[PDB]
Every structure is written in structure tokens, then in C-alpha cells.
Image 1 (spheres, rainbow, N blue to C red):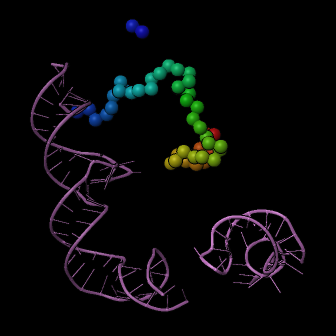
Image 2 (tube, helix red, strand yellow):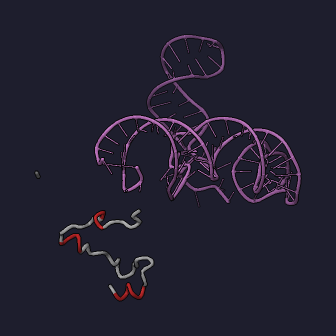
Length: 47
RNA sequence: ACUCUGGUUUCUCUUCAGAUCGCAUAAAUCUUUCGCACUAAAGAUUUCCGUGGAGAGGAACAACUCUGAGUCCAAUUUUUUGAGGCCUUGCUUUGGCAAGGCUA
């Protein structure tokens, strides 16, 4: 109301102190959908 | 149910495309804005990767699939009947016509 080949940590976004946005509560999709590439047994463990 | 067009594939040449021409994303020049410009935004122009529409030429085989075109009802409800004969009046184009009353 009022050369550097790496990327610096000051360029980061989503540094927001919100209880709703840090824990964004991702979906699991009826226990049937899977996130691609991440290991399926590990996804069945972390559900 | 009988016949006549139109093929597919590949190569090359010439035109049009601000259509997500490309369900992906490059490089150069100029101007402006600030930093002090690879770690930066906007505008304009240009170069390369290669594509869709149309037309023309070539040559390898299939010729009529497809796209077209030329080529069983008689019995209510319609097409298997209620059909034909008589009289009066206006005109008779003296053949009969129009209206009404009849018999079947």
C-alpha cells in the first residue's frame, strides 16, 4: 500500500511465507494417476 | 442389374500463402530505455533451418474398389363405382346447357 555458469539463489521465486502455498497439496488422482518418470514403487510408497 | 471420366508413386521447374504457414524455435543490423549489456526489455528491418495451396514437364505399374455420370395394391380411406332414367323453369349454339324437385 505504500563467468558465472551457475544460477544464483537470489534469482529464485516462490519464496512466499504462506501456509497455503508452501504446502501446495499436490494431487494423487484417484490413486490411479502417476507422475511421470519418478519411480512407480516410490510413488506408491509416498502416497 | 449394363457402360465412360477421374489413378497411385517418385523427380524437377514456376507462382501464392500474417494459416500455431513450423502443436518446434535460431543468428546478424539499426533505434529507444536503463545499467557501469551474455547474465536486458520494446520496436523496425534482414539472413538461414523447411513447409502448405496451385500449375507445368518426366517416367514405374494398375486399369474400374471408390468418387460420379450416362442407364408384391378389387370388398369403406383415394385406382376397380351408386352407377343410370323422370318432371319444371331462363336460353334454345332446337344438340342440349344451368338450378331445383324426384325414382333407383
